[PDB]
Structure formats: C-alpha cells, structure tokens
Amino acid sequence: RFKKHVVQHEETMQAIAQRYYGDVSYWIDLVEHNNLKYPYLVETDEEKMKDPERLASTGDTLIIPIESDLTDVSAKEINSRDKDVLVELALGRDLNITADEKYFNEHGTSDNILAFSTNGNGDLDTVKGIDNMKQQLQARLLTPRGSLMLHPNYGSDLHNLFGLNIPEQATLIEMEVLRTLTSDNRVKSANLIDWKIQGNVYSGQFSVEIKS
Amino acid sequence: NEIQDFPAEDVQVIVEGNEARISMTVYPIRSFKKISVSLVYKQQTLQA
Image (cartoon, each protein chain N blue to C red):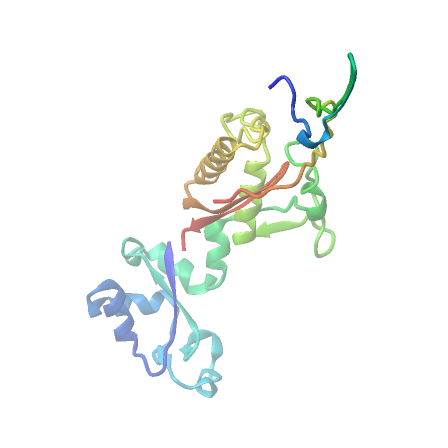
C-alpha cells in the first residue's frame, strides 16, 4: 500500500522522507520507488522535457510507500515502472457487468438483471479502480444473503426488509446497508448522512471510507 | 331541560265568561341527525 503526494515549489527530496517517515536517511531508497534520475525533483518543466519519464517537477505526483514495503525490493521494482497503474492493480481488475446502468436501477432484488457488455473492440468490457469497487458494492447490496452457489452468507436481507415505513424499519434498513458495506475488508467504515421518507419511498445516502 | 327554550313574550290568553283560550310557542330540543366528513390523505416527510 501507498500514499499519494505532489511536488511543491522548490521542495527537496530530502524534505519529503523526513516529513512522512521521520528520518531523512530514507530518501535514498525512496527515489528508487519513483524511478528518478539524479535531478530527482527539479523545479522547471522545460527541464523535465529533457527526458520526461525519469523525473518529477513542480506539480507532479509522487508515490510514498508504507514503511514495511519501503525496504522490499519487489515493491521497489513494481512502483518504479507501474506508476499510475498502482491504484488499478491495488483495487484490482474485473469484468464489467453494469451494461444497463439505467435498467438495473429499475428492478433491484430481482434476478437476471446484470449482463456482460463490450467496450473498445472485440473484447468484453472490464472495470478497474474505484469504479470496480463501486460496482462490487452495488452487486453485493443487490444480492440475497444465501444465493451464490459457494461461500454463502454473502449479500443482504434487503429483499426481506419491506415494511410499514415506520422509523424502526428505517434504522433496520440503515443497519443492514451498513453491515453489507462494511463486509469488505478494503472499506474502513460506513456511516449514514441522510435518511428521508416520501410516503411509500425510502431515500438516503451513505459515506464510505475507502483506503487510500 | 325538558324544553330547549320558549319565547316569554309569545303567551296570549283570552277569557270569556266560563271559557278561556290559550296560545304559546316552544323551541323543542333540536336533533343532530346528519354528519358529513371530508377525509384527505397527504404525503409526509420524516428525516434523520
């Protein structure tokens, strides 16, 4: 895992390692992760134009490992070249099945609702990054608790919670949604920020803390 | 309370030898026979 950062005006590479990891001494290993040539951070972009991929300048992103992966040579090699592909790999890659986004939001808690799609040309669509995490939360919420053919106790009792719209039913629904969202270890916490009623319609929203 | 009201002004009586004739007015207790209702259902909000 890693933290994101950006190059500030005339910040030296010594200064970053000292602020995040404490000891300045660690900058030496920290430059290999960002694959930098000797002018590790340089102010001017027309100087980055010298050989763009092997440098960082003012306004560019940087990668900051956690201290345990700082010394790992494999983490060094991977972070050297992958660069922005970090987030995608770290959140993982999967087949996209939100083909009919307008449609699956008309019949949730019913089956047969999702389907493969095609993007690009001649290849099934795929999803990655934060979109993948959303899609997976979405599918997990719209699936009943014991309906996947292996590893059951997956999904929700959202199909079971339909009731007289009195507030206790609404707190129950809130708690089920929060449990469902907090099931995945990748997510830190969820919390409600609004619940709202319109006769026979529930509405509400939840904030979820995704790890960096 | 056997009568609701009566106009005290409206008592007229005439006597003629052995014979008398009387007239008066009484407000009887009024009933309450019909009730109509207009019952409406509305949306409502409840919130966090």
